[PDB]
Length: 328
Ligand SMILES: CC(C)[C@@H](NC(=O)[C@H](CS)NC(=O)CCC[C@H](N)C(=O)O)C(=O)O
Ligand SMILES: [Fe+2]
Image (cartoon, rainbow, N blue to C red; front, side, top):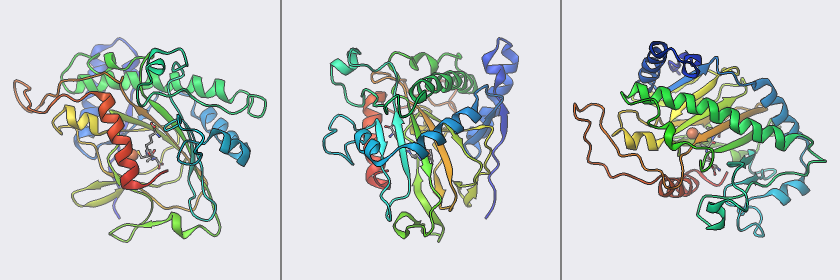
């Protein structure tokens, strides 16, 4: 019933060289991360009007033929190499949500991780240029725009924890990041299929159940339709929508590294019968990236938790999320 306190943080100093101003941003990241776990990043420099318009044009013009040709393995047995990247189909009358996921544009057939067949690395699939002119160029450019924003955010998290600003960002590299963009369409449907609505223990109608994120951080743009709720000790609280800002939260890899000092907030998606967009960028590191866990509450920072390689974390995490909350 209540509304979550989600502050709006001007992140523009993180692109600059005024070190005190960066510290003032870091303090606000720290405070939000220790409270509900969510904040809006504002003054971020990304053209989100164009993001939303180009995503809508793609979602509304793609045909069933094209969806089959781009489908991940869960929907097309022919595409055994597409576990992450491709189209995630809706099922008329049963499943409302549909989406398109793409990975690092640098993952080509000649990339060494692709040649080694390393798990979680795939080459992106794209629609025909002539049916969707400019879409691939836009989407690859967007990847690097949100990469740049995420790199700056990571400097803020580092300073917030008392570390040098490259503590996380040094592991977040264009040549090997496992980060993904997902372009999700939540449709207006009348009648809305009952199989696509889940009922929470507390009676709330949901589109996606409670979870912690599989990410270091999650950088999310959504249309202006309220849908997210965050769990607190006193129950779920509504996150108000803001279609000019990016909603930021930590994933479970951050909670692991920090001995839960920055928790991964549990959140869920309420069912709303409205046409809307949900466009997450999941900040993932490289396959071999390892950050030694530390405990910010302890003077010496010592913690007993085992270091975890990002690749093993991600592979287990994505499968666990499918098993718990369903194939999307
Ligand atoms: C809550 C939003 C981020 C969005 N949900 C989501 O994106 C949910 C929960 S964080 N995320 C996932 O299913 C993980 C997708 C991972 C992606 N295929 C990849 O290979 O990297 C929604 O609107 O449902
Ligand atoms: Fe999430």
